Amino acid sequence: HWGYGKHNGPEHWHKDFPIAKGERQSPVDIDTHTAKYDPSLKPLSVSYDQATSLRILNNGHAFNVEFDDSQDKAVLKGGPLDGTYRLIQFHFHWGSLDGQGSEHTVDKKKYAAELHLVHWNTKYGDFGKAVQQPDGLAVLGIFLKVGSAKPGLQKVVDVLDSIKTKGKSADFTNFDPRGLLPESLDYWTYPGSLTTPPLLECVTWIVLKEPISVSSEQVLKFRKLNFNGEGEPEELMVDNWRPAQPLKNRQIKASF
Ligand SMILES: C[C@H]1Cc2ccccc2N1NC(=O)c1ccc(Cl)c(S(N)(=O)=O)c1
Ligand SMILES: [Hg+2]
Ligand SMILES: [Zn+2]
């Protein structure tokens, strides 16, 4: 099944998942000079005060912090979005080297990594029904750069030990995702897709302009994770990122 290697990577996904070549695929290059400041766009509202994390899983491509999403607690609304969207999970995409890893790029610039907080549209009942809808998901993309430690990431950094290999999960309660946000909520927005298979075209993307900084030691630990399961030849979880895809007529809008 799919991966990020020479024989199962992004260039191979289209065969099992035809939509890999579809009309609204992610990620894309954000051409900052072509993106249009949109005044019809209400301010963003990120409300993570009640967010209830349950666990962190190595899924064989990334690790997911998962959230209790059967009540309205950690919610995204405002900006490009109509109604409310509930936080289901967060995860990252990173490189082997500081010079790559982000999925979205900004005037062709690849950041060291990118965080996705994944939210689903409440009017659709649950995650599984939302991903059948064109406005089913909202993902908040946040860029990572290597510099100072991000304090609010360190609790994730240290549990990674427990979930080195594919399949492993660990209890991960009381994590506050607010720690992971930059100061400014300025963003770009476009209609797009999951960046992994099934690659469903159900996402409103909201990519924040201001990266967070993480430390070199922080990113390094990310890179100690494994693509293989326990007992297998060791493939190191690096370069788990899809490259930029064709914009295709679509317009990216700036919130600023
Ligand atoms: C392990 C698989 C299986 C699965 C099931 C439900 C939700 C996410 C999810 N997975 N992982 C993802 O990384 C994922 C899910 C949704 C999205 Cl919107 C994205 S992403 N990369 O467009 O932000 C990733
Ligand atoms: Hg969809
Ligand atoms: Zn992602």
Image (cartoon, rainbow, N blue to C red):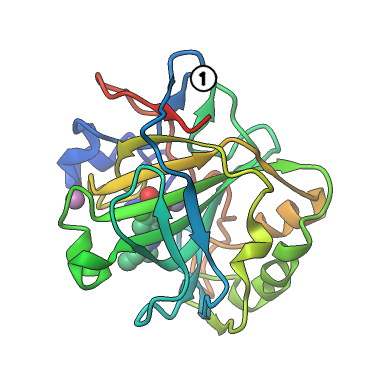
Q: Residue at x 37, y 81 (%)?
A: 71
Q: Residue at x 29, y 43 (%)?
A: 193
Residue 91 x/y as whole percent: 51, 59
Q: Indicate if the residue with disc 1 has its beta carbon within 8 Å of ligand 1.
A: no
Say whether residue 69 is left or right of residue 151: left
- Identified at 48% across, 35% down, the residue is 104
Q: Amino acid at mark 1?
A: Thr
- Residue 141: horizontal and vertical position, in percent? 50, 46
65 shown above or below 206: below
Between 34 and 160, the one nearer to me in the picture = 34
Residue 51 shows up from this direction:
yes
Which sits in the foreground, 143 or 208? 208
Mark 1 highlights which residue? Answer: 32
Q: Position of residue 52 (x, y in %)?
A: 52, 80
- Looking at the rendered structure, the secondary structure element under dot 1 is loop
In the figure, is residue 220 to the left or right of 44?
right
Q: Nearer the viewer, residue 20 or 118?
A: 118
**Drawn side of residue 161 relative to residue 247, left or right:** right
